[PDB]
Each structure stands twice: as C-alpha cells, then as structure tokens.
Image (cartoon, coloured by chain):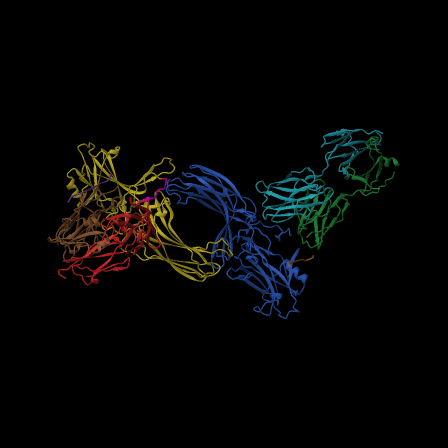
Chain colours: A purple, B orange, C blue, D yellow, E cyan, F red, G green, H brown
Amino acid sequence: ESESSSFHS
Amino acid sequence: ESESSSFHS
Amino acid sequence: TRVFKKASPNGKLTVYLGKRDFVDHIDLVDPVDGVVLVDPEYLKERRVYVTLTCAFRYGREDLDVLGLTFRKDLFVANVQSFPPAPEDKKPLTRLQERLIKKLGEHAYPFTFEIPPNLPCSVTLQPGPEDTGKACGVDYEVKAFCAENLEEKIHKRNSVRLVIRKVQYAPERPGPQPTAETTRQFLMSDKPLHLEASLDKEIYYHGEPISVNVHVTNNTNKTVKKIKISVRQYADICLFNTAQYKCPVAMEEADDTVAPSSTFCKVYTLTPFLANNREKRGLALDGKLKHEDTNLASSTLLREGANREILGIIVSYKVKVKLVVSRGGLLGDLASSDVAVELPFTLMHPKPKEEPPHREVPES
Amino acid sequence: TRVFKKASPNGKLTVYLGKRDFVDHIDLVDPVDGVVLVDPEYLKERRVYVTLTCAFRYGREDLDVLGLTFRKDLFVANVQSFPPAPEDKKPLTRLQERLIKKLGEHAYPFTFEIPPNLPCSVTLQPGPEDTGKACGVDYEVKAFCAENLEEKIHKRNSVRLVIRKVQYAPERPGPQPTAETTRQFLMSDKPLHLEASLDKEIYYHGEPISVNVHVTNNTNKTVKKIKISVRQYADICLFNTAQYKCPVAMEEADDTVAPSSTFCKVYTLTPFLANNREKRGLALDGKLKHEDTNLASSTLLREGANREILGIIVSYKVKVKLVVSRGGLLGDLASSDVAVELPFTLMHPKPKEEPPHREVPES
Amino acid sequence: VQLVESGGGLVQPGGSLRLSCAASGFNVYSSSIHWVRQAPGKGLEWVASISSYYGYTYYADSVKGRFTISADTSKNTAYLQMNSLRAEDTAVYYCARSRQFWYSGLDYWGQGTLVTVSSASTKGPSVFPLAPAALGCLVKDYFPEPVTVSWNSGALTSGVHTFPAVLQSSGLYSLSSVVTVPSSYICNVNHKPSNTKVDKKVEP
Amino acid sequence: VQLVESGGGLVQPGGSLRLSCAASGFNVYSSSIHWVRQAPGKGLEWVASISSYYGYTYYADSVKGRFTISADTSKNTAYLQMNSLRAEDTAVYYCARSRQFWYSGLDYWGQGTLVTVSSASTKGPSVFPLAPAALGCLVKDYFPEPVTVSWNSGALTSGVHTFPAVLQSSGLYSLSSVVTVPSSYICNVNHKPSNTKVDKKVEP
Amino acid sequence: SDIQMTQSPSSLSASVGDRVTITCRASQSVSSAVAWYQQKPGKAPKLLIYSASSLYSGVPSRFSGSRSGTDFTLTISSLQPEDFATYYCQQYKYVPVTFGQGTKVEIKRTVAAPSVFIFPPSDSQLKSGTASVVCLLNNFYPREAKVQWKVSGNSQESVTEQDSKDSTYSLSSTLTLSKADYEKH
Amino acid sequence: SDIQMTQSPSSLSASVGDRVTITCRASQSVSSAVAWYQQKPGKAPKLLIYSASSLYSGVPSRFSGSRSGTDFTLTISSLQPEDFATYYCQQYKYVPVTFGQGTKVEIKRTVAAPSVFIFPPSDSQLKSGTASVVCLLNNFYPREAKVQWKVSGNSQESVTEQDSKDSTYSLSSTLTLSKADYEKH
C-alpha cells in the first residue's frame, strides 16, 4: 500500500 | 335548393 | 347536356353554371363562365353584381358564442353584369351562347378569371362536438343587385353557390424515390446500413403501398422492433407558419436482427378513414355541405418557385424506425434508434367524362 | 512536509512523490517531479524505466467475461532514470534535492511534462451489478527495470501509482447569463414572452441555485404547468461524437397563467448524489480505488481553440419548460410548449493548503 | 380480374349458410361489394352491400335483422351472414364488384350460385311409358333437380322435345320429354342426386 | 452564521425528547452536522453525525439502537431521536457544524443545552444556621438545581464563599456558602424551581 | 325512399336489323343516375350503358340510349343475331337498390300451325293410383294459344324454349285427377 | 476500530509568559488528521489548530504545535492571562470520533496557609434527626491537602474555584451521621 513518510528537517 | 336543368337541342 | 341553376328567394334572379368543379393544370385554370337571369322591371337598383371569393372560414375558441365562425378573405374579385359595361367585352363559350339563346335577351353573361398560385379546396375534419359550418378552404360565388357596392345587402336579395378547385395526377411519373441511411456507434467502427424504397411515387386512393427494406447490421447489438408508418404533413399559413403531423396507419414488425447479420423484407400499409374517424383535425378534400369525402389528396405546388402559398399545403411521407437494444457503458442514456423518411405523392386519375358527385347511394 | 512512497513486492524498488494531485492552469500544468530508489547490485538488467500513461480503460459488454475491461492508451511518455542519461539534464526542485540528499547516492530523480489540452480525471458511475475496475479517465505512473523496452515485464518487477488531474474555479467571474424567449401563434398575433436569469454563472457544489423567471402571456390560452430542471451534458470522444443527457434534479410548479396576464417568481434546486444513486452512468470526479466523490465538476476547455479534445468533456445547463393547454382548430395536434436553456459553470474554490483526501471519516 | 364464389347448397328452413366471395385481381379497399338475388322466373333483387373505406353497412328491408355481411382485408374475400332463412328466399345468388371512386354501375359479376331452402327430402324418380306421330315419357314425384333424360341411350336425337320441370304443390318435381316418330322404345332417364337410372319402354 | 438549539428538559428515565438544531447563515447540503455530549465533571463525547449530501448516518456504539438523527432541508434544521433513555445519559448536549468539502475540524458550535434524566421529583430547600472568624449556612435535600443564595439580601458581599452543589446518594442536592467575619445574620436563599425563598439567621 | 320503375313493353319480337326502342320511367326525379343491363339465359347479367347515356368500353356502337324528363329510352339500330336476350334499366340515386322487371327479346317468325296430340295415361297408372292426362302441342307460332279441356283448374303447363332449328314453341298442358273422377267419364 | 488517546500531563500551573508544552499520543498511525480545542469553563469549546499543524484564522500566533511519529505536541510561547483554560487533542482519521480527557491550565501562586475551621451542627439539627459535621479550609495553595477526621468514608467534599481576588482555594469536607452515632462521642 501507499506509505506515509517524511523528510525530517 | 340545388335544382337541375338542360338545354333541349 | 344538363346544367345547374338556382334562384333567389324572391325568384326575380336566377344564375346558370356549366359545372361545379374547375380543373387547374397548375400553369392555367379553366375559366369560370356563366349567365345570370335578371328582371330589371321590378328592380330599381339598376345595378347587378357577382363575386367569387376565396375565404378561410374558421371557428372561434375564446369567444363563448356557439356557431359563430371567423372568416379571413384571401382573394375577392367582383364583376358587374347589369348594366352591360362596354369595357367588359369578352367572348362567350360554346355553351354560354346556347344558354343566352335559350333564355333570351333578359339574361346577361359573366366570367371570372382566377389568378394561379392559389390554395385548393381543402376541409378540416370536424370534431365530435362540432355543429357549425365546415372548416377549411372553400370557394363560393355570390350574385346580387344593389344601387352601390357599399349598400347594405339583403338576405333575400342575394344567392350563394359553392364551387371546388381540385388537381389531378400528372400523366407521366418521375423517378422512384429510394432512401438509405448509415449509423455508426462508439464501441466499434462497424457501420449500420439501412435501405428503403417504394414501388412508385404515384399511387391512387385505397391502393396498397408496398415498400422494400434491407438491413445491414454490423455492430454487436441486436435489433428488437421495426416501426413502419406514414403520416400526414399539414402546412397552414394564416398569420404564421404552423407545422404539425398526424399518422394515418401504423404497422409493427416483430423482426429481430442478430449482430453482424443482414435482413430484407416487404410490408404493406393502406390509408383509410374508417379507423381514423376519431382523430380530430385531419385534412380532407372539398366538401359541399356534409358529404363524406376521401382523405385530402396531395397538392402540387408551382414547381420550385419557393413561394409562400397561403392556406393549406398538404404532403405525405413514409417513416421507418428501428428499435435497438440498450444497456452497456452508457446504460439507458443514449439514443440508438435509426429512422428514415420517404416522401410520395397521391392524387386521383383524370376523369374521362363523369365528374365526381355527391354520395351516390343516398339514404 | 510528509511524502508518499511505495515499494515493489520484490522490495528492490521504492518511488517517492510530493503529492497525488496536480493543478492544471489550462495554459500550463505543474511539472510532475519525483525520485526513485534503486538497487543496482542485484539488478542485472542495468536499465530502469518509468512511464506516465493516459489510457481509457473501459469495460466490455458483448464479451460474456465478467470483470474484463479493454484499455485504450491516449498519451504515453516514458523516461529512463538508470543509467543516468547525459542528455536528460534537468534541474531538481526544492523538495527533490532534499529527497536526493536524504536518500543518498542510490536514488535517481525523474520528471514528466504533460502537454496541455488533455482530458481531466473523470469517473463514470458504475451500476449496481458492476464488480470490475472503475470506468473513465485516470492517470497512473509505472516504474520498472528491464534490459530492453520490449522485454516482458514481471509483476514483481513493476509498481503502479494513480494520480489525478483536476481544475479549479477561476478567480474572476464573468457576466451574468440571462436568456429570453418569444413564442408567436397563428390564431392571434400576440407574442408570448419569457425571461430567465440565474444569480451568478459560478456556483459551488452543494450550494442552492436560484433562478429569476418572468412570464408575459398575451394569447388567449392558459399556462398549466411549468417545468424547471438541470441536466448533465456528457461529450465523449473515443471514436466518434457521443451525445446524451441526464437530469439531476427536477422541480414542478403548479402555477397557472391567465390569458393576457403576466407572472414572476423565483425557485431553487440543489444537485446531490443521494437521490441519484440508481441513475446508471453518471459522470463523477476522479476516484482512487473506491472513494465516494462528488458529482463531476465542470471542465474548462482552452478558450475557443476549436480543438477536438479526446476523452470526456462535461457541461451543465438549466432547462425551463412551459405546459400550454391544447385544443381548438388543430385540436391536440400542435406543439405549443415553450422552453429555454441556461448554461452555467461549477467547480471547487482554490484550496489554501490542505489537499482533498480519501474519505476522512473512515469506517 | 376474376370473381369466384362458393358455399351454396340445400338447407332446411330457418338455418344458416356461408357465402364467401373470393375476388382476384384487385383489392377491397378500392371497391364496394354488393349481393343481388333473382328468384326463378323472377327478376334481380339487391340484398346487401359493403363499403370497406367508409366502414358502412347497408341491407334491404325484406332481409333486415336476419342478414349480415362481413369482409376480411387479409384474404381479399368477403363472407355473408344469413339466419332464420325462409323457404321463399331460395334463388340464385350473385356477388358483384363496383368502383368506389366512383359508382358507375355493376361492371364485374360472379358466376352465380344456387341456394335451396326447403324441408323436403330427396325423392326417387318415377318413369311411366306413354303409348301412342309422337312418343313420350313422363317423370314425376322426384327431388331434387336435375335429371338426365335420353332416348335409346342417346340414339334418338331427332324430334326429341325435353320440357322444363315444374314444381307442383306437393313439394316435388315433374317433367316430360317427347319425341316425334311418323310410322315406326328406351326412355333413358337418370337422376343424379339419387344416382338412379330408371329406364322404360313405350308400346302401343 | 449562528447555530441555535432548543428542546432540552428534565424527563423520567426511558422516555424520549426532541432536539432541534436550527442552523442559520448556511445550508445543510454543504455541511455535515454532528452531536457531542459532555457529562458533568467529565470530557466531551461524540454521539451522532449526519451527512446530507451522501445520505449517510453514523451513531456511536454506546447509543446504538436507541438513538436516531433526522434533518429537514426545508429550513436548514435537524431533529435528534432518542428513546429508552438511561439516567447515566444526562449531560450537556451540543450541536456542531463542519465543512463537508472538506473535514477541517469542528469550527462552529452551538450554545449547548442541559438534559436531566432522573426519576426524582422536585424537593423543597432546607436552610439551617451555622453557629460560630467565619459564618456559614447550609442547604440540603433539595431538587433540582440551581438555587439563589445571598447574605443579608446581598448586603454582605465580602468574604462570602459559595460552594458548588453536590449530588449525594439519595438523589437530591446540597450546597453550603460561608462568609468570614472577624469580630461582629440573614441567609438570603431562594430556590427558583420551587419559587421559595427560605431565610435564616445564625447566632452564637 | 323506395322507387317503382315500370318498363314497357313487357316483351316484343322483331326481325334482324329492325329499329327497336324501349321505355323506362321513374316515379321521382332521378337525374341521370340510370344504367342498363342485358342477361343471356343461364348466365350473369352484362352491363351496357351507364349514366343513361354513356356506353361501356368494348361495346358495339349499335347500342344507343336517350333520356327525356322522367322517361328514359334505349334504342338499338341494327339487330345482330346475338342481341336476343333480356334487358333491364336501373337507377342508382337513392337506396335501396331496386331493379325493374325486364324485357325479353326474341326473333320473329311466320305463323306455325299448332299440332295437337293427346296421350291417355298408361296401364301402369292404373296400379299407380293417380290419374293424369297430358296434351301435346308442337311447332306453333306465336307463343300465345288457346286450350280446351274436356272429358276446372289444378292443371300444369310446361313450355319449352324456341328451338333454334325450328324457332317455334311446344306446348304441353297436363291435368291430374283421382281414379274415381277419371272413371266418371 | 477504536482509538485511545492519553493526554499528559493531567494538569499543570505556571506563571505569566512561561513556555508550556503538552503531549498527545496515538494508539495507531493517525497521519496528521489531528486537531485541538480549548474550552473556557461554562462555554462552548473553541478550535485552535487543525491538521495538527495548521493555525485557524484569527488566532494569536503565540499558539504552536508539533508532530513526531505517534506523539503529537502543542506548545505555547507566551502565556497571556486569558489562556488559562482546558485543552483537548482530537484525531479524525477513523470512526468513532474519540475525544480525550483534557488538561486544565491555571495560574501560579505562592503557597497559602490553610485556615482550618470546624462547625458543629446547629440546634435545629437535633430536631432534624440527622447529624452532619462540616470543616472549613480557606485560602490554601495548592489544591492538594491532607484531611484528618476524628470525634470511615461516606464524607463529601466541595471545592470552589480560584477566587480571582486571592487566587486561592477553599476546602469544605462534611460527614453525615446518625443521631445515636453522633451521640456516641
């Protein structure tokens, strides 16, 4: 399925 | 009313 | 040879005419000839006037008055017979001179000359609750004597006779009208072909009508029903063009067409008034007082003159329709039916010697 | 901010995108930017390919196979990421460079650029008996690695992500659409005037629609019923032109108009899917897998270019009809009804920061 | 254009019958069909008429209430309804065609059919010699018509004078045939309905 | 944009009530309406919601089977159905409005209404003096809330410490108000539901 | 309304090529809605003239007709041998369709002597129980004749058609009787 | 499925202008479909932040929030005097809509000496038939306190809100008893 990731700033 | 006649010849 | 006549309620006036029907050859019209009997001794007006009038008598809806009909004159021409005008010098026909000889020196001739491009004798079929006069186009001739044209006319001092203006089928037929249609769909590029053709463009009243139809189905759908019909196209021009249609006879065929398959057959229809009595407003041919007539024969116009003819213009067409199964991506939203129209022409053949008369088996 | 990612069933590949919706300003479209993660150590094909495809997947009716849908591609463009082509030199966006920094040297960027004048994301409402995929226009992105383009693709060796192409309501409204009609009859020369006008050509989904109507009756007839409706116009471009209509909501007013009298009033209609669930084939906005969306928003073409846009084009209209009493000389043969059409435009306002998501109150 | 009719026969009084008028070469929608009868020794007499286009039915006063007409457009054939028949109604019946646009007389006529309305039953022929110039042979008390009569099985065809049969008050028929012989046999007589050939000789 | 609700009251357990949520400044076709409750001394709690566009109804598990929601598009007002009410269900009820395109929280809230579900009946207030610094006056065994309490008919407003009422196990209410007097009267107390003003004096 | 037509004369005989005329009358005005028919013995009637003046297609021109007020006339110029049949005048103005009685036309011949024969009943009549006597008249012209019976009705007459070989009639009158009455004289 | 959120700490007190933070936890993945509300005592709740990061229109900028995995954070930079109320964390990803317990925020004051008073029942209580004794504690900070009863439950407590004039609490514990039990000692 679609995964919800981020880019930690 | 509508009557008829002729010309005897 | 016998002739028609009628007298005023006073009996001092009498008019004589050769016939009641006047043939129009499209290009020209037969001259209307006649002679009137006069009694100048009793009449102090000393002037005699006759008139032929083209008027559209029609009933009124809004007014609550029963029996009253409105009438709009379309063409009025009047000629004075007595006293004999030296300017109105005209020849007399073979019968007219004989009539003058028989009646003597107290009878005067008269003649009107109808300009061409005029509506034919047509009557609208009255409804069940109708008790007034006929509705449609009708000619009449009125003869009277008065001191002046504008003088008030008396009911006892005038006469009224009705005449009819009819056409006949031309001797030479033309080409056979044939029409074809082609329908394409969205799911596939296979076209839907249809052909329709009649026997001949000219038919007689009461004869069977046979049509040839061929179907070329190439799509994946199936044809359910095939609708064959012929309708009456009526054109009326009183103040504005009003267009309306009415079918005369319908036949339904239960033929089914498999996908990517063809079909051919022939069917027959017959128009008649017996099953269409209740259909209000149908166009009918000329009526004298109440005689039952056939369906209104087709009117032949002045070629391709593109004129705006007043009155009623009648025509007929042949309608063929196909019912196509629905469903699929569009569901029941599209309109997949296919139709085609075939015009044709219908009159009476030329009479030999006998003119049509009024309901021969009188009861 | 947060981003979206998905991995192949093999787990070797993972693709990252900034969003799933892409705004088209008609004239230009937002560039589609992204980065893919690659594992060349186990990857012996030495080549990696990504593709954005505009295809019209569509179900099939004649094929008795349930679930089978035919797919017709309309626009396909593919770009290779690995190995890095020296010719495909492109700048990286502000987020794209940060993503490359985060992932490292084993991630490669990519970018497609959609040409304008292309169909938007539209979905056809499936019937109650439908169990296959969605019907309509939908974009998707597929990424994979292969030795050659023509090489057979493996299910474990590819991914598929769906994106949407939507429009937004322009900020500057236009003039107010107002339409008037005038009908004349044959019995009398008095005309029949009608005026219709909406509030504003731009509405939002779920807002009430108010129309101003004025009637000038001058004839002798009486108006019986007044029909107000709005219908969905669907233009389909697959092989030919496909035209059909479907109403969304109808209101009937029992107003009667006396002869030679006027009238004026205002009515309100509201479109919503709740009462139109059973209406098969309705046009709906883009769906991801099964999320319930609103009615298909109106599509704004690129001015008057007269382009023959492929796919589906949607529009709306306002229909007002008048029922006129029959009878009289023509009886029930004429067609005296009067109608008018008012077009209008309906979209979504510009979102501020939050993009629309998938059925917030999940059950 | 050929007009064909069938359905006649002999029926007891008060019954019913089927008269179908099979017309060929033309349709019924353009023609008006009429029925006319003629009693033996009498003149013609119109009984009924039909109008396909106007759907109008007309009947004579003498035959009102008991007679009805019908027509089928599919087969271009018309049927005639009769009920409660009277013995006096026996005659020869004809179906005719007339142009509906317009009436111009009765141009087309059928072959004609014979109907017999009587309670009498078939009777055997009776043959009697006639002694004497001329020679005769009488046939009486027989039913129904006709009979086949010859002299010497057709060998005497000179001077033979067969006479038309007569209906006497007993409801049977009788006739006589005579032949002239100056100086000088076999009365060859056959009755087809009874299929009986009764023969006799005449002697002084 | 103003949200107005009405229809609350005190009902015996197991009954029913009418909660009408009158919305103004907006329609229901573009918004989703929700109901939330909060028990006294407890937190908020969602009970029901309605979706006009999709025609979908949602209810909490604790209130399933006994609660139903309804809405009228004619005047942008919705009604709430409750049946077989429980005494524990008494709380403060709120009607809220949320954007349907799209969900962005609960921006708009009503004024809130109080519902009481108890079989207890109204009880008369009881006033007792509190001899002694500080002076007090106790009120107990009364129903329902609230009461109006003052000292010297409002002439002693310094040091007065009215305390919130408490529900004891007998189903009635009780509260106490105290005032501080260093050296040195009239416990002006009124119960609005009973419309009874009972007054007392405190002496050493 | 019903209409009665009297056609006169009832019947006549004439030679080949003679000028012959027939008169048809009407009880009321009928205008020119009058037609004529001819029927040969044993066959269907054949139309000759319609509208009282218009010849049908394919007819010999020898046929002719005329109208004078309430009286109508049909005239034949030359009498062909096949013109000897029955004729009728018909009106078609008012219902019901009422026909006339008709005139039969026959050839003309010289007077033929009636040959009188008498045949007494046979001996088989004695056992039959019924007595009948028949008299024979052969080759007599014209058809009318006088009969004398002697040894008073209930007697039958049978007359044959003109035999084209002789163009003469044959008369046969018979009288039935009982046994006792026959034996009376 | 149901989602349970635990808000910590339960309650705190601080001085004006301090930086305060709150922690919101999730039982499962909730993405960023999380919002916050503040409710003043006796009024309707007021929305502050939606999507766990987006400030509402018209809010002072001193409000702030943060997200970190399954733990969500809201932080206040400067404490305005009107910011002392109750706050709640709410998620809106899955039904049902499940609220939290809430945190009460109050001002900070110095320690206040609890003044202890005891009030024996009045003489009218003798005729009432019920015995009750109530002790008075006034102007004490903070809320927590120790109570000793002597002459063992069924005793009630009524605590008033911070009096803004003094910002101190008042405690009142009462114990009902029967007549004989009261007369025991």
Name the quarter where the N terminus of chain F is drawn. bottom left
Toward the bottom, the furthest residue is C44
F1 lies left or right of C100: left
Q: Main secondary structure of the magenta part?
A: loop
x and y percentages locating residue E199 in the rendered image: 77, 29
- The reply to whether the magenta stretch includes residue D123 is yes
Q: Can residue H70 be spotted in the picture? A: yes
* Residue C182 picture location, percent across and down: 42, 43
Number of marks in the rendered image: 0
The answer to whether E184 appears left or right of C313 in the picture is right
Q: Range of the magenta residues?
A: D122-129
Where residue E11 appears, as percent x and y from the top left, is 69, 38
User: Relative to the observer, which residue lies in front, C220 or D266?
Assistant: D266
Q: Quadrant of residue G150?
A: top right
Quadrant in the picture for the C terminus of chain F? bottom left
Q: Does the magenta portion include G173? A: no
Residue D93 appears anywhere in the view: no
- Where is residue E71 drawn, in percent x and y? 60, 43
* Residue farthest right in this picture: G185
Of residues H66 and D341, the one drawn nearer to the viewer in this rendering: H66
Instruction: State the residue in front, C317 or E94.
Output: E94
